[PDB]
Length: 271
Ligand SMILES: NC(=O)c1ccc(NC2CCCCC2)nc1
Image (tube, rainbow, N blue to C red):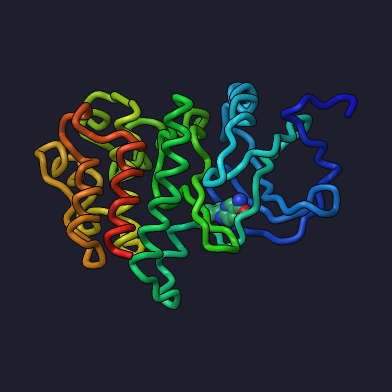
């Protein structure tokens, strides 16, 4: 209503129900909007985000809508901390979900998680929108077991320089292609590379990529042309798909449309 733009939610419409955890920007809670609608509420710690830039970008994110993309519902920016209001994902972070061995996943379920993410990324690619930090830690799982891509583009607004460049202690070295580590060249093809690593994370049930190496050692390994190798649960065909994401030459890496086709083909053959 009065005083709120289309990208703005009235925080008074929120009912807080459960604490879900704390991440980069701070706490995330489960709640309801206007009594009935499930939402997640991301409370953005003061000093952690370039807030004016993020708010302008939220207007763009409002228009991104895909079944495999965690939906942005709006922002609460009239006070601090500001809130980001999103779709609720009852089963939490993908990385944690993978690591719970009780699920006893079939490989068909693992491939479906990859397809979920690939569909979201194909959609983002169709909108010329880069994720910029794709990884299992940035995917979420709903009550139906569907994986969705989360926090797309949000790394652009992080003020902690330890996260923001390779010269940083918290940069996602293990999800970055050589041209990012060497020259900071981000593109659709750096998202493609990251997606391959995410496939590896899924098929590895949430192991850390290059688990015996430091970040520094990982950068040397990949810049020297070496790669992750095949997770035990990945068939040859699945391995071929993730490996294709890691061509040294960015322009030899597939698009998300091509990866989706390849994933569907393997589903059909492995079903
Ligand atoms: N959209 C959601 O429902 C939702 C659910 C859990 C969650 N967990 C985060 C994992 C990393 C630490 C902070 C909590 N983040 C978002």
